Structure formats: C-alpha cells, structure tokens
Image (cartoon, rainbow, N blue to C red; front, side, top):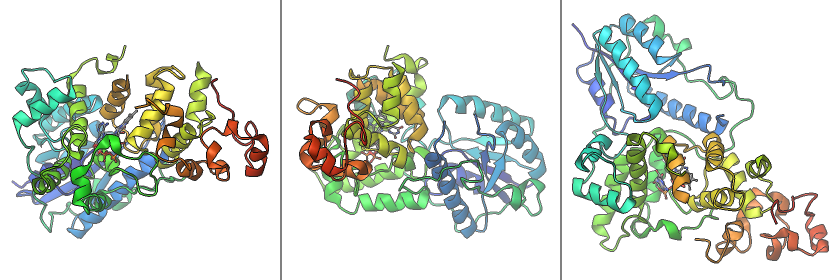
Length: 450
Ligand SMILES: Cc1cc2c(cc1C)N(C[C@H](O)[C@H](O)[C@H](O)COP(=O)(O)OP(=O)(O)OC[C@H]1O[C@@H](n3cnc4c(N)ncnc43)[C@H](O)[C@@H]1O)c1[nH]c(=O)[nH]c(=O)c1N2
C-alpha cells in the first residue's frame, strides 16, 4: 500500500545528475540509500584508491544527513543481503545506475531475478556515460565504430548528450525506524584502518562529490584555458599545478557527472568560437572515455585486440636508473595519478621496445595503484599505445623541465645533482656525484639497460 524504495550506489557516488535517486524518492514513504561493501576484500588494491572510495562515501553520508536521511553501508554480498532487506523493509522499488562492466552485468542480472521473486520493481537509468552506449551501437548499424574520428562522427550525428538531471529535493524520505538491518553500528562508513590496511594513503587528491565540483569550478575559472585546451601540448612535468584537470578519479567513481562536465564545456564553447575541437580539446577527452567504454562494453574479446621478470620488477619498484622514468613510477605509487604523457613515457619504456615484456603486466601494476583505475580506460590505452622524435621516453621530461624540478620532487636523492646531469646522472663527473651526495650504484642505481 506504500512505496518503500532502495537507491543502491555502486558508481554514481553523487547527488547531482542522479536519475536513479530521483526515481526512488518520487512518492516514496521510505527511501533506503545503500552501498554494499564486501568486508572480505582480502584475496591487489592500493590504500590510495580504497581510501578515495571511503572518502567518497563519507561525503555522501554528509549530504544525506543534511537532507534528513543517512547512507546505509551494508556488509556482505548483494545477492545475499538484498532478499533479506526486501522483506524486512517491505520494499517495492529498487533503483540503481546502469553499469556496463563485465562483472556488473552478472551481478545485476542476479539481483534483478531476486527483485522479481519479491515483487520489487527495478529501474536502471543510464548516467555513468554521456550516452546510452547500446543506442549508439544500434545507430551505427549494430557495430561500435573502431576509430576516434568515426566515433566523433557518430556522436555528432546523434546530437548532444542528455542534460544533467535536476538536483534532488532538500528533504528526503528517511529509512524506517528500528529496522534491524539499518542499525547504525552495522551500517557506518569504515576507515582505511578498519578495512585492514596497514600503510596510510599518501595521495593529495581527496574523494567525494564535493571535492569533484570544487575541482570542476577551478578548471572553469579561466574560460580561455578551457576553450584553447589541447591535450598534446600540456606539460607532463607540472606537479605543483598539474597541466590537466585531474578529474579522472572523480569521473571513474561517479563523484562527477560526465553529463554535467559536457554541458559546462558547451557553455564555454558557445562564447569562444575559436575553441579547440576534438580529439585534442577537453570535450575530446570526454569523448576518448566514451569511445573506449562503447568499444569495450560491446566487444567480446576486448583484451585480445593487441595480439624477463627482472625488467618488470625494476620498472615496478622505480629503480630503472632513468630519473624521469623512476620519478613517474614514484608518482604512480604515491599519488595514484600521473599526467597522460607521463603514463605514455613509462608505458612505452616498458612495452614499445625498451624492456619489451607484455603490456598486460604493465596494466596490472596500473590497476593496483591508479586512483582513476577504470577497467575500460586502462586496458584500451595500453593497446592503443602500439612523440619521442627528438627526446626518447627516457629523457622526455628534459624538453619541458631542463632543471629537473619534477625529478627532484619525487626522487629527493637527486635534489642536489646539477641540472646538466639530472636526467643522465651516470654521466656526471664522479666528483660531482660525491659533492651531490648521489653516487651512481650506491645511492641511485645505474641504468638497467645499455
Ligand atoms: C597506459 C595508460 C593508462 C591509462 C590511461 C592512459 C594511458 C596511456 N588513462 C588515460 C589518461 O592518461 C587519463 O584519463 C588522464 O591522465 C587523466 O588526467 P585528467 O583527469 O587531468 O585528464 P584531462 O583533464 O586531460 O581529461 C579529462 C577527462 O577525460 C577523460 N580522458 C582524458 N584522457 C583520456 C584518455 N586518454 N582515455 C580515456 N579517457 C580520457 C578522463 O575521464 C579525464 O578525467 C586512464 N584514464 C582513466 O580515466 N583511467 C585509467 O585507468 C587510465 N589508464
């Protein structure tokens, strides 16, 4: 006789542009905001990324409490928890954002069956991508386009992505009182210590929808920078103020709506007729993401499109002996984010013909440490790898940073090396090494390859 609904967060960790949340609140006597956390994640995942998620859930908790509700972090597996709470809470509707990843399809199909057995309606809107990816494939005749230029042609044919959804109401229907499965002590957001991590996170990027919107506003503080953006011309050695938006972790977890980002770019583009165009523009960057999601989700053998241990270990542990390479690998572990062309440098130095190895092994290392780790974006970018015309990937940074400021920041052992040798410290006169307190082979390794 009443509507009791669940809004289930997996991605889409936001209140803004959340059509699943708007549906669950409509005409609802009680709404249960749920995140399902697998407590036994022990089995691979850096504390930096997991803490980013926890911070994002803490932000959601604060947002829901401001509106008379709270987030319920349920422990267990969705297939076991949901049948119990469907009956306990008298649920009539279950809402959640659509997800096209492989595991998500298996998980969501099972939950859809359990909902039907309990008489629960399921509503799953598209809001993680700009477009309904299935719709794009259908309008392309039933096959995903295979080049960026062709893909940009198709979306231009389709038109603008949908507008961001309205903000939710200032007050929300709360969960019912004294429901055993909603008890606060069993449903709070845990800390990185409580989930089992021993080392603290070191990244400088904080999770959550609130920080995402703050960072988006900062990127749009200069419309001329947004209008003139060209990805290949940005500086990979810029760390104090990165040369790109660093919105990737926020888009990965859904703290930031891709649709809101796109709408804001078109606002700026209307007033700047000479703005950059795809693929180098900031809109092009969003379209790279959409392109790889579309191809990845509709391609069965997606990982097969691109056709010894010691070299990988040195690369993994930032001891290759090339300061530019080791500095980036240090940024990976410490920040979990590096500029696109820094990612290119270490990836080419690993796969494009310096250490050979297999690109899959390099992806595994990225998958552990990147805070923007994305099943589709990580793999696709490794394969699309297969710029250094003058500067080889091992001294690439010298073009932008002849003094080696980036290297000195992340490899402080080299902080007193004269700039003439900071990219090739093995060339320094051996008394220069002594003076700088950095002897090659003692304080910093010699190059691992001739
Ligand atoms: C080896 C390797 C591995 C990865 C990636 C590249 C390479 C070469 N990338 C892509 C890229 O390096 C990354 O998206 C940016 O460095 C993120 O920086 P900004 O958010 O400042 O991007 P910037 O502000 O330039 O772009 C804005 C947004 O567009 C998207 N975007 C930009 N460049 C992209 C690209 N090349 N491919 C797809 N989407 C792109 C992202 O959503 C990004 O947040 C990736 N990206 C990611 O989100 N998760 C990942 O796990 C990886 N892994």
